[PDB]
Image: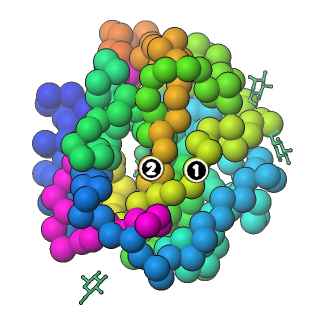
Amino acid sequence: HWGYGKHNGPEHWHKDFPIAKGERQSPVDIDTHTAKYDPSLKPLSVSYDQATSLRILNNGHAFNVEFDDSQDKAVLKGGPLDGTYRLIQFHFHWGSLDGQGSEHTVDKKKYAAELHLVHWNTKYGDFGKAVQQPDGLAVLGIFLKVGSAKPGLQKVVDVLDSIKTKGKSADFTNFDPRGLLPESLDYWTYPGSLTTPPLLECVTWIVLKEPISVSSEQVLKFRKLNFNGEGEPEELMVDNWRPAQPLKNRQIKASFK
Ligand SMILES: NS(=O)(=O)c1cc(F)cc(F)c1
Ligand SMILES: OC[C@H]1O[C@@H](O)[C@H](O)[C@@H](O)[C@@H]1O
Ligand SMILES: OC[C@H]1O[C@@H](O)[C@H](O)[C@@H](O)[C@@H]1O
Ligand SMILES: OC[C@H]1O[C@H](O)[C@H](O)[C@@H](O)[C@@H]1O
Ligand SMILES: [Zn+2]
């Protein structure tokens, strides 16, 4: 039922999901001047060398690239995190035009899109148990701006024609997510939530400061996907982002001086 349209979008979600008005909702605006360096943060470790991708799915809201999370392979450690978090999937949020699409904003500036690499805390055994815990998930967020092409994104772009409509999937083995990172791992971090229903308040957000550049042609292909299923009237999959939510009783910490 929930979506991004006028009649089922972010301003309606609270009726079924009252936590939408909660105390640690995401995304937020990142005020870079108020964000403070945190010396208690440990070095961040993104260890994706043995990642095993499996499948790509159009779920009617975005597309997910899914990974084998039955054992410790691609993991995120360090930074603000206690213990080991396993990669389960990544997806994007994007706009109808280059001037909007990100969920987090930086001094109110909206990027063209935002990549979310989703990980769960292995001390809870499964993703479903992890989303019953305050520290169950860690999402690594990466901004996309439009400029030069990102070579490591092209394999994703070129499979999208095969998953145009809701419910379609395709094999997506042997994809290396290391090709989606920027050079620097400088980041901001804060406690938040899932940005889509069920909006659960389980996430440690780690948002990289350096955006990746993708080409106009790459993001234009994201915008050819459909929210609807096969045979149904075409609704382009665009503007699948939630706007910034109140910061409330939180502080954003920076990894860099
Ligand atoms: N968009 S998000 O990364 O917060 C996200 C991740 C997830 F695993 C499930 C969700 F419902 C939402
Ligand atoms: O195929 C994508 C990636 O898969 C990983 O499991 C391999 O260890 C990497 O060498 C490879 O780049
Ligand atoms: O009481 C002082 C403390 O206030 C907190 O809000 C800040 O996060 C700390 O960095 C600071 O040392
Ligand atoms: O790596 C992701 C995918 O990239 C390309 O589409 C390859 O043709 C395919 O075999 C692979 O699964
Ligand atoms: Zn997301």
Question: Magenta stretch containing residue 253, yes or no?
Answer: yes
Identity, as a three-letter code, of the amino acid under mark 2: Lys
Measured as percent of width and height from the top left, residue 142 is found at: 48, 44
Q: Label 2 vs label 1: CA separation?
A: 8 Å
Q: Secondary structure at mark 1?
A: loop
Q: Which residue is mark 1?
A: 184
Give, as a single range, the part of the protein colored magenta: 237-257
Residue at the (42%, 17%) spot, across then down:
223
Identity, as a three-letter code, of the amino acid under mark 1: Ser
Q: Is residue 12 above or below residue 101?
A: below
Q: Is residue 24 above or below residue 60?
A: below
Residue at the (46%, 33%) spot, across then down:
144
Measured as percent of width and height from the top left, residue 63 is found at: 51, 32
Q: Residues within 10 Å of mark 2 (few under 14, many from 20)?
A: many
**Dividing the image into four equal quarters, which quarter contains ligand 5?**
top left
Q: Which mark is residue 243?
A: none
Look at the image and tell me whether residue 170 can be seen: no
Q: Which residue is mark 2?
A: 209
Picture quadrant where residue 70 is located: bottom right
Q: Residues within 10 Å of mark 1 (few under 14, many from 20)?
A: few
Q: Is residue 17 above or below residue 146?
A: below
Left or right: residue 109 versus residue 61 is: left
